Image: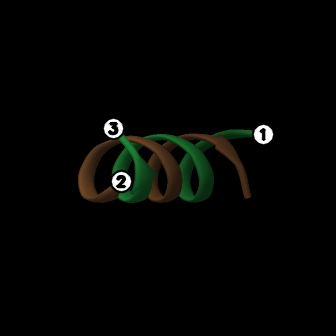
Chain colours: A brown, B green
Amino acid sequence: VGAXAXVXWXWXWXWX
Amino acid sequence: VGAXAXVXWXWXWXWX
């Protein structure tokens, strides 16, 4: 859990 | 729905 790559919020694919 | 900033899969904060 924290910051880097995986799922949550930030930059990538999913919901805007 | 698509790519950019928000919630989903990629880089940011959450679960790895």
Seen at 36% across and 53% down, the residue is: A1
Q: Chain of mark 1?
A: B
Q: Which mark is residue A1?
A: 2
Q: Which residue is mark 3?
A: B16
Residue B10: image location, x then y, percent: 38, 40
Q: Nearer the viewer, residue A2 or A9?
A: A2
With A6 as the anchor, is B8 left or right in this view? right
Residue furthest front as drawn:
A1
Q: Secondary structure at mark 2?
A: loop
Residue B2: image location, x then y, percent: 66, 36
Label 3, label 2: how many angstroms apart (C-alpha)?
6 Å
Q: Amino acid at mark 2?
A: Val
Label 1, label 2: how many angstroms apart (C-alpha)?
25 Å
Give the vertical position of A6 relative to A9 (above or below): above
Of pointers 1 and 3, the one earlier in the residue sequence: 1
Label 1, label 3: how many angstroms apart (C-alpha)?
22 Å
Q: Residues within 10 Å of mark 2 (few under 14, many from 20)?
A: few
- Camera-near label (1 vs 2) is 2
Q: Are marks 3 and 2 in contact (CB under 8 Å)?
A: yes
Q: Nearer the viewer, residue A9 or A16?
A: A9
Q: Chain of mark 3?
A: B
Seen at 78% across and 39% down, the residue is: B1
Image quarter where the C terminus of chain A lies is bottom right
Q: Which residue is mark 1?
A: B1
Residue furthest left as drawn:
A4
- Camera-near label (1 vs 3) is 3
Give the vertical position of B1 relative to A16 (above or below): above
Q: Chain of mark 2?
A: A
Q: Secondary structure at mark 1?
A: loop
Q: Secondary structure at mark 3?
A: loop
